[PDB]
Amino acid sequence: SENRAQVAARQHNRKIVEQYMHTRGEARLKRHLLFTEDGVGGLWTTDSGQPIAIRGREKLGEHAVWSLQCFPDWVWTDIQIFETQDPNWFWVECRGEGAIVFPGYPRGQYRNHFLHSFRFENGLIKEQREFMNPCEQFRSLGIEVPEVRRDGLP
Amino acid sequence: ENRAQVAARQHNRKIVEQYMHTRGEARLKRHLLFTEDGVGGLWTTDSGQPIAIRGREKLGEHAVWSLQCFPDWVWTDIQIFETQDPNWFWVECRGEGAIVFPGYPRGQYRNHFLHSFRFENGLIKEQREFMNPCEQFRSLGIEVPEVRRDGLP
Ligand SMILES: CC(C)CNc1ccccc1C(=O)c1c(-c2ccc(O)cc2)sc2cc(O)ccc12
Ligand SMILES: CC(C)CNc1ccccc1C(=O)c1c(-c2ccc(O)cc2)sc2cc(O)ccc12
């Protein structure tokens, strides 16, 4: 029953995506338990052009300690979960917001639009990736955003 | 109900495939894949507001400018994702080509992209693309600010 197995995987994996996206507050300290032991999470859109990949369940748990300090009230909002033809691959469109308390920058408020990719193995997240426009994070940190000159464009 | 959803998804997938493969002079007719009131454009920009091109006529005009400023643009590494909504698709891909922006040195632009396609009655109602604008800054010779990471693990 290939189809039955795929349907079961997709329904379970959707519940894990829902739980990830709704993880807030102190529960963030245990979000890494939604990953495989060698699972990877992180931010694929950064200033430098290289992803910030947090590799393995142990490092993901450490990242959560940092995130609770630097993003103390972070929430995902406007959550739309997309199943796909691959029962082990989901996409999520959402927004996120909260205070930003980044080391060495003034405290501020950060709001952005996000896309997330979730790939699963044996019922847990093998790879989570998030994609956003870093210019909005620059603005939240008081960093000047470059302005493309548009005079020559329609 | 299921038969109508399956029919829609299979047809719409072919339109996404056609859109993603469109290059060269065929770009001048890509707007014909949209509804008359369809919208396309870039949702991730320096200013923080989307550049939305509204209506099939304006989309056709944009293609003229695109062939000037991105004369050889190709989408590569195309992965199409169907969803539970037969009228909504996502695409993960890369793109590459010369960038010839007015008042900037000619450059080469490469980036990773996500696209969203929503359909109505067999045609694209809304196309949106999402990327990291910092790579487009680099292709234009624009300095990218650097977030200080010393205080981070
Ligand atoms: C709740 C979310 C808004 C948290 N966000 C992140 C999530 C995952 C990875 C990195 C970040 C992040 O915020 C950035 C850096 C960072 C590096 C090391 C580290 O241990 C912690 C954070 S460096 C950098 C540069 C940018 O241009 C944008 C973001 C980040
Ligand atoms: C093949 C693709 C790489 C084409 N790309 C675009 C697609 C749709 C919309 C805008 C762009 C674009 O490239 C930007 C601007 C632009 C504005 C008006 C116009 O008629 C033509 C282009 S302004 C700006 C600022 C940025 O920071 C990044 C991109 C753009």
Image (cartoon, coloured by chain):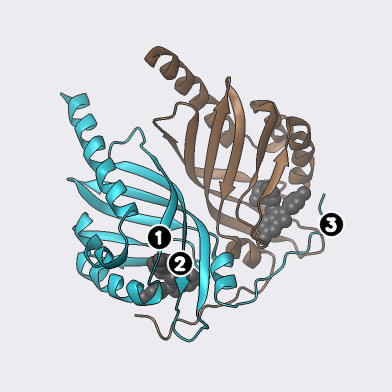
Chain colours: A cyan, B brown
Residue pictured at 15% horizontal, 23% vertical: A1
Q: Secondary structure at mark 2?
A: strand
Q: Residue at x 44, y 53 (%)?
A: A77
Instruction: Say the numbered circle drawn on residue A152.
Output: 3
| Tag 1: amino acid | Val
| Label whose residue precedes the other's in the sequence (3 or 2) | 2
Side of B65 where B121 appears, left or right: left
Q: Earlier in the sequence, mark 3 or mark 1?
A: 1
Question: Which of the two residues, A145 or B113, is positioned nearer the viewer here?
Answer: A145
Viewer-nearest residue: A25 or A149: A25
The number of numbered badges drawn on the structure is 3
Q: Nearer the viewer, residue A2 or B5?
A: B5
Query: Disc 1: which chain?
Result: A
Tell me if residue A48 can be seen.
no
- As measured in the structure, the alpha-carbon distance from the residue carrying label 3 to the one carrying label 1 is 40 Å
Q: Amino acid at mark 3?
A: Gly
Q: CA distance from mark 3 to mark 2?
A: 37 Å
Badge 3 residue CB within 8 Å of ligand 2: no
- Residue beneath the point at 31% across and 66% down: A25
On the image, numbered disc 2 is attached to which residue? Answer: A98
Q: Position of residue B91 (x, y in %)?
A: 48, 41
Q: Quick check: is the Cβ at mark 2 less than 8 Å away from ligand 1?
A: yes
Vertical arrangement, residue A105 with respect to residue A61, above or below: below
Task: Determine whether the residue tagged by mark 3 lies in a helix, strand or loop.
Answer: loop
